[PDB]
Figure 1 (tube, rainbow, N blue to C red):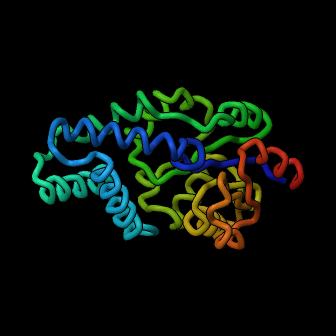
Figure 2: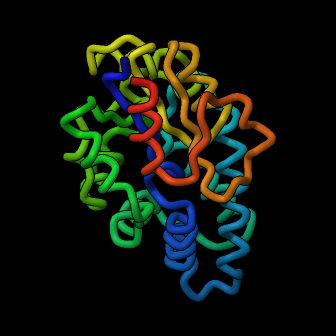
Figure 3: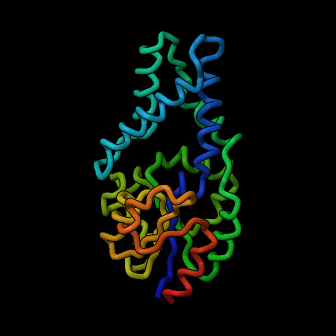
Length: 230
């Protein structure tokens, strides 16, 4: 029987369309009147941070702040604008103000609360994450929140999942993990015996659906799956 349901954060609860908008605001703030197209800078930032995170998958933890600052310093040098020294402060500020959760998130977390342990498992810098979840108003909807900084490794390393399972007092087989990346999320959670649910809102990752136990396009499908398993 499933006694716990765990969720990834960015791309699973936090809207992808919303972070794009948030990220565009950060770029515009960074640039000011500098004659570089902010959308061009955004596109470059996304790509370079995506590639950087990629190298760290499954490896010991390194502050995400450090990895993103590295990229931004490289881009300022590349385009000739000055790297803002308070970049990370800017980064947090924009996230708190323009972040948007997918429409059904609160409904789903609230419905599972009480029946199941509701947790979050995410590759994140802990302090920043807490400030971010607070601004979004959901920090308190979780029974546990586990980060790569706590575990000391990035998904799909098993230690991050093990720590989340231990905080909740459940074995892997009694837990579900909901994420949006088939290999890091479904692949990583499966190593602990957990049941994986892939969130693919636009059906864009069919090539990898076979890596996951279940695929959903809306988070409200999660409680139906849990009842069905129980």
